[PDB]
Image (cartoon, rainbow, N blue to C red; front, side, top):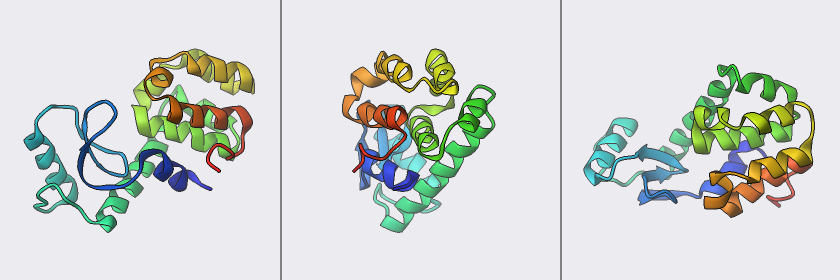
Length: 162
């Protein structure tokens, strides 16, 4: 199991524009297009992202290319974030993937907002951290995904994904 595989399981793959759990226009492997309500806006964004006129449909290759860029961006955001970096540096490989998953989903900023939890990860207090993480809009809106990531922080294995 690795980060790509993890995230493919969490986000799925769709080749046509769709609405994510929050209602935002999205495509491919969890690729957010725009927070706005306009389908036009979304098509526009897609065209600019792919560099071609798509009529809102993309190929699998095109889907993986966006995903690869999206995973690389998340890592780097983490790595360039004052709050995030120290935490990532402190974790083992499995637990690193779990933080990348959060960032991919909710952004650097959103994650940077889980102060208490983050401090707990830095001290290796896996159970206290899992409880704190669950106390969040994130856990209450998308519980099955959040359970996965959280168990991964708790145990440092891929069991939730297997």
